[PDB]
Structure formats: structure tokens, C-alpha cells
Image: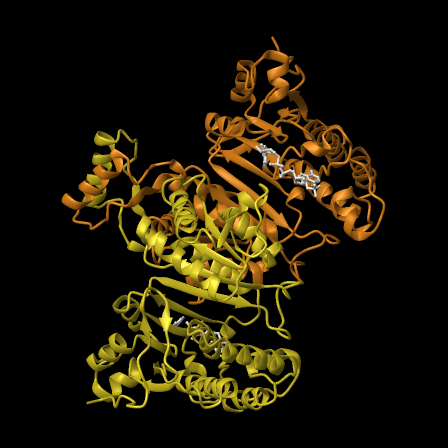
Chain colours: A yellow, B orange
Amino acid sequence: MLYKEPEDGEKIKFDKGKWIVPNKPVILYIEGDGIGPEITNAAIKVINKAVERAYGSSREIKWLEVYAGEKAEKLVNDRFPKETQEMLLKYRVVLKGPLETPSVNVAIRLMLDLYANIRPVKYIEGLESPLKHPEKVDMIIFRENTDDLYRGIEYPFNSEEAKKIRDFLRKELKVEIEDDTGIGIKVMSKYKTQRITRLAIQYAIEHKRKKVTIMHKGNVMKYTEGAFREWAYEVALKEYRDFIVTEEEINQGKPDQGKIILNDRIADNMFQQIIIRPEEYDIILAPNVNGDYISDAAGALIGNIGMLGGANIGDEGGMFEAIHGTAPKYAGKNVANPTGIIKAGELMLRWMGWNEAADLIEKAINMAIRDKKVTQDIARFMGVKALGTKEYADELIKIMDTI
Amino acid sequence: MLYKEPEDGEKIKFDKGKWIVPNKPVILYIEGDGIGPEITNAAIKVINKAVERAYGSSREIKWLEVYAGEKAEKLVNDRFPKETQEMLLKYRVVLKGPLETPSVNVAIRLMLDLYANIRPVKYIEGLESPLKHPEKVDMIIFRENTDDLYRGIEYPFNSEEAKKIRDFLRKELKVEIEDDTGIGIKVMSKYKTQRITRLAIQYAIEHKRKKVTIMHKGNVMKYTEGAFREWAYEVALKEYRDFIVTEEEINQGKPDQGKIILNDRIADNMFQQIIIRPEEYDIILAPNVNGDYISDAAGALIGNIGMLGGANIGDEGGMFEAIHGTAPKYAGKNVANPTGIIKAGELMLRWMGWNEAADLIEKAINMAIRDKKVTQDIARFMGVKALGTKEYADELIKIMDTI
Ligand SMILES: NC(=O)c1ccc[n+]([C@@H]2O[C@H](COP(=O)([O-])OP(=O)(O)OC[C@H]3O[C@@H](n4cnc5c(N)ncnc54)[C@H](OP(=O)(O)O)[C@@H]3O)[C@@H](O)[C@H]2O)c1
Ligand SMILES: NC(=O)c1ccc[n+]([C@@H]2O[C@H](COP(=O)([O-])OP(=O)(O)OC[C@H]3O[C@@H](n4cnc5c(N)ncnc54)[C@H](OP(=O)(O)O)[C@@H]3O)[C@@H](O)[C@H]2O)c1
């Protein structure tokens, strides 16, 4: 066989969207292409120190590397070998480096049905920003990632399918539509909306987040994004009644002191407020297309998109990756910045409920960057000698040793 | 007749989209609700000083007030009187203050087929900003405003229409869709795309602009946003061949000296770059939804939406207004900032080819701010005494008399 499963650890379990983690959970990891190996191994080192520094030996991640991408092709002549697939369906938790494509990421998300795209973006003390006052940027985007126009139901204007549609709309729905038109079908599912929503609220509860904001354009798209809003409130008030409190209730007399706030904002407003007063957002709940855009903008609030981490969560598993590519320019040069993959580590740790260790990582990074101990991607702007990938991780390690 | 048309003026003519303006053009204006009267009259006063200062007496705007809104309800018992519609269909150019929606804006747009939403947004020395470096922010968003999901072709998840759509797509096109789904139809028209593109390029030529960037999400919406991109390039490479050069051609060998650059960016990249380096944008050519969102963000860059002008333009007419509302709390208190509407007039002036008057207005505003001579909405932050509406306008007038 290709992989030797660590007979020392146990697989993570899920009763109903909730993670049940063993003290020695087996976690898979894929180095990635290009800078992948250098930054991933660095992260794994940092994660371990953080785990031992927070729990001593009472907890330990039993890492299991699997092959995917260029390394897999070179070893077994298959970019996504069957055995890799088997370990993924069996352990379902993976930290993976960047993969190039001319799609492993797609396949993984689909076989584990990771419908929720999670994007946390928090300001890091020390980093330059395009914003004058980003000190309070501490939000996390929950993007439904299987619905909306991403379904791909569209047709060219000169196609026969488009014609059948125009014809059908004119007769049955009495809707007027010209011939020179491209056509796409925007779909919004109640089940899909209730899924992400339940996940967004459960997350707020367990991590003491104080607000969930539903992003939508329900005034022009009443039955798609409008319905998204409705279904979101609906399931929130029916299944999390004792934990939440709408905004229309707060300014209605009801008490919110000790509960999670749930409000909604028009797409337009958010694209404006994220720039003017981003501190207003805590958890952002959005359908597929809006969350994609909000994430791009949110992500831009802080310098170097390469220091952000993210994930794809399903009801029984998750994939954690940095928000960047392979950067073949630096492959094997010990120059790339591992903060991105490390932050995916921070995120994974939080999902696992191992917050003490995730806070250690978050704290060491803050301290290292404010202390001018950074990689070239940052050093090149603060006039200092950049640290290498390996040296930087180690600096994070010794820092965690005394905080 | 209810309206006394100035016998000294002439209507503005139209040739293939080109505004043919007499020296004594008649221009309709609507005071609007709330601060409308105060700000609109001040705009007219500054616009007339700009025109005069730039062209002495050889040109003059023959202003014609028409009634719309609550003033219309009060004088002739009609929110959008018949006499007003007739003046609009005849003169086709109007400067309109903010109107409270209880409708008129949409009705004017439709009756004049003003399909293009135009939003210029550029930095003003002295104004606060969310960005640390807004200095080179100087762009104009050209939004197609009659296509896309705004057409309203959508249906509730439990309507009989929705089930017909699901059945149709299932039997005729073989598409799998669950029953608990809201359904919306995104339409992208070749002709609507082509005309907005003609307007943008034509504006670029006319005003010595050098770059047109197409905003789209064609990688996921290939036949709608993607077609918008293809179609835009098409009309550009075929009808303005010796006026523009594509980004592909340039970084391929083609010389760009003496030509307008035409390129395209994926929507998500623009939500990032508009924040990190907006200076990279000149003219943004986008379809309905994208343009809406980018505009929201764009105008958020200056941080005083209430100082932005905008317009709706067709092949034979234009509506110019401020991006703010009726601000009822300040109605008739001579406190409201008139820069928004004045800016709308600046834009009207440029569309008329009266760039000299327009430049005067822009320079005056820049100076008034630089010299801390502003209305309260700005005084608040620069720690100086505030000028009233009336006084801020007379100051701009005092300034244009020196530049
Ligand atoms: N989740 C994923 O797996 C994922 C996501 C996006 C893209 N990709 C892949 O990336 C490949 C091409 O890369 P790209 O050039 O398109 O995006 P990239 O690999 O992310 O390179 C983008 C730029 O950002 C900087 N950068 C990226 N990672 C960095 C790091 N770890 N440390 C410091 N700086 C970093 C580099 O700045 P410099 O100019 O200083 O070199 C580089 O020029 C594509 O084939 C695509 O498949 C994968
Ligand atoms: N083009 C249009 O006709 C148009 C556009 C937008 C909205 N509206 C209409 O406005 C109506 C209600 O008003 P809204 O409150 O919804 O509009 P708004 O855009 O929200 O105007 C009110 C608020 O925005 C600020 N503001 C707007 N213009 C200002 C100015 N010229 N100077 C100083 N501050 C200004 C003020 O903030 P501060 O209190 O801090 O000074 C004020 O409290 C709606 O029914 C809607 O239909 C019309």
C-alpha cells in the first residue's frame, strides 16, 4: 500500500455538523505544488508546538501525509491516486498546500461535500494596509459554495437551448425576451440556505461570536436572494431561538444582552460599509456569488492576501488551505511566507475546538510581525532583513515558548 | 400652458449619440424634495457662473423648471404631471434634485430610454477618506442599467411558474433541479451591451480618457458576463479600430501611444484592486449587477457619497442627479451640502462638450475644500466653522472668478 495509517491515532467523528475530536486525531495533509512542501511542513511544525504548548502531551495530532498533484503524478503517475481518495473519505480532515491546475481542490470539496466556504480575515498588528484604520477588522465570511449561478446552468445566445428557453418563456410565462440574449439560470435552494445558516450560527455559539449578518440583494432578486434572507431568519428563529435575537427585535425592546445578533444588509450597503466601517461585521452569511465578492473585498482590507487562510467545511469534514497559489517563482528557495497555510492551521484548530492552540498561533504571528521578524513579501516594505520560511516558522515556535 | 418655455433658447439635438448643443440650450430642472430646492438652486447659480466665466455671454443655459414629486402633487395634484412628461420628451435633458420614493426616477429613465448609469468618482484634496492613499483615484463607471437580473424575470419557489420552469428544464434540457428552489433568469443582451460600449468609448475619445476596463465574471458565467466581455471587445475592435488598442495587443508588441487602452478584469479581482490601487482604473465598463456593486465600493473610496454626482444617459437625453437622498432633517435649513448636485451639473457640462465650464467648477470645489471653506458635513472633521448651503455656493462663485 502507499500509506501507513498511524496506528497511534483515531479518526475525527461528527454527530450532526459538530466535530467530535480525539486527543490524538489523525489529520491528513498534502504538501502542495511549488512552495507547498516548504510552507506546509513549516505550518505542521508550528501547529505541533502550539498543541504541545497548550496541552502538553495530553493532545497530539497524528499527521498522515497523502499525495496529490505534481508529487503524486511523479510518484505513481496519477495526480489524485485512489488511495489518497480513500484516506480522504475515511479521515475527512485535511490541511493542504496550494495545487496548480491548467482540479484536485474541486474533487476534494465534492467527494467530502464541503458546501461551506469559510474565509476569516482579521487585521494583523504591524502589517501595512490600504485602510487608514483597519485595527478593528475581525470578521469571518460564511459562503454557501454549491448554489447560485455557480451551478452552471447557462447557454449561449445563438444556441438551440437558448431558443427553447425564449420560446418557453414567451408562451408559458408570457415573458418578453429578445433573440440576441445569453441566458443563465440563477437557482437558490432552501435546503442549501438552511445548511450554511445552521453552520454559521453553530459556529458563533461555540466561538463566542456576537453577530451573524445575512448579505443579500433581496430587493431586486426577491425570490432568490430575498428567499435566502427569509430562509436564513426562518431556520435561525426556529432552531436557535434561545441563542439569537434579530436586529428588528433589539430596536423593538427585546433584550440581546447575552445572545447572538442576527441582522441583514443589502449587497450595495456592504460593499460600501466593508470599506468605510468594516468593524461592523462579525460573521457574514452570504449566498455563492455575493460571498465570493465580499470575500475578495474583505480580503483586500489587509495587506498581503498571501497571509490569509480559509477552508471548505461539510457536515462531516473539512479542507484547510492558504489563500494563495503555488508561486513557482520561489519553489524550494526557503523564501515564501508560510503565514497563509499556518492561518489555515489556526482555523482548523478552531474548528476542532482546540482554541487555546489557535490563539497561541494567532498571538505569536502578531508578535513576530510587530517585532519585524517577517519574510521577504513583508520585509521588502519595512526596510529590514527578511527571514526565510524555515527561520520564520522557528521564530514563531520560540515565541510561543514564552507567551 | 403650465410651462413658459424660454423663447430665447433651443433644444439640444442628437447625432448618433453625439450631443449637439446650441449656445442657448434649454435645460429642464427639478428642485426635488427636502433639501432639493436649496441645493438645486445653488447648483444652477454656480453652473451659470462657470458658463459665464468660461464663455462670457456667448453661451447661456436657458433653465426651465418642471414639476415632479411632492411639489407637483401640491401644485397640480400629480406626482409626475402630464405637462412635465411633455417637457421631458421635448427637451430631453434635466438636472434633478433628490426625490422621495413613496418611481419618478425610474419613470424618467424609461420614458427617455436612459440606459446608461454613469458614476464618476475622483479624489478631492482635503477630504477625509478610508484609504491611506486616495490621491490618484480618478475613474468613471459606465453601468449598463436595463439588462441583467434587474429585468425582474424570477419566481417564488412555490409558484406555479417555478414548477413549469423546473419541469421544462428537466424534460427539454435535462437539467436536475430540486423543487425547493427560488428561480431567477439572468438575461444578457448583445445589443444592450453594444450600445453601452459605444457610449463608453465615445466618452473616452471625447474627453481624452485613456483606459476602458470591462468588469465581468465570465469564468463562471460564460454565456452572460462572458458574452458581455466578448461583445464589448467586438464593437470596439470593429467600430473604433483606430481609436483603441487592447491590453493583449500591447503586451504582444502593438504600440499604445496615441490610443485608448481596452482590457478586462474578472469581477473578484476588481473588488480587490479597487481597494488596493484604484488609480489603475480609468473607465469601468460593467453590466447591471457588477456596475451596481463596483459603484457602491468606488464611491465609498472618497467617504462622502453626498458629494458625488451621477447620471442616466440614453442616445437622446440625460438625467443628472446627486447620489444622495432628500435629507429631510435639513430641509430648508441652509445646511445641506450642494456639491453632489453641482457635481451632477459638472457631468452634464461635460456631456454637453462644455468642458471649460466643467473644469472651472471642479477646480473651484477643490480650492474651497483646500481652504476649509465647506458645509457642516465636512466642517465636523476638520475642526473649522461651517458655511451654509447658500454661502458655500457663493464661495465657489467667488473662487471661479479668480481661476
Ligand atoms: N487554493 C489553491 O490551490 C490556489 C488558489 C489560487 C491560485 N492557485 C494556482 O496558482 C498558479 C499560478 O500562481 P499565480 O501566480 O496565478 O498566484 P500565486 O501562485 O498565488 O502568485 C501570486 C503572487 O502573490 C505572491 N505570493 C503568492 N504566494 C506567496 C507566498 N507564499 N509568499 C510570498 N508571496 C506570495 C507572489 O508575489 P511576487 O511578485 O513577489 O512573486 C506572486 O507573484 C495557478 O496555476 C493556479 O492553479 C491555486
Ligand atoms: N436620486 C434620488 O432621487 C434619491 C437617491 C437616494 C435616496 N433617495 C430618497 O431619500 C428618501 C429618504 O432619505 P434617506 O434618509 O433614505 O436618504 P440619505 O441618502 O440617507 O439622506 C439622509 C442622510 O444621509 C446624509 N446626507 C445626504 N445628503 C446630504 C447632504 N447633501 N448634506 C449633508 N448630509 C447628507 C445625512 O447624514 P447626517 O445626518 O450625518 O448629516 C442624512 O442623515 C427615500 O425615500 C429615497 O427614495 C432619493
The residue most toward the top is B1
Q: Is residue A243 left or right of residue B339?
A: left
The residue most toward the front is A242
Which residue is at the front of the view, A155 or B241?
A155
Image position, residue B229 (x, y; %): 38, 51
Image position, residue B35 (x, y; %): 70, 31
Image position, residue A232 (x, y; %): 41, 49
Residue at the image position 22 percent from the left and 42 percent from the top: B166
Residue at the image position 52 percent from the left and 87 percent from the top: A53
Q: Is residue B6 above or below residue A242?
A: above
Which residue is at the front of the view, A252 or A107?
A252
Q: Image quadrant for the C terminus of chain B?
A: top right
Image position, residue A29 (x, y; %): 35, 82
Q: Is residue B171 left or right of residue B5?
A: left
Q: Is residue A331 above or below residue A180?
A: below
Q: Quadrant of residue B360?
A: top right
The residue most toward the right is B385
Residue at the image position 18 percent from the left and 44 percent from the top: A160
Asked whether residue A312 appears in the rendered view, the answer is: yes
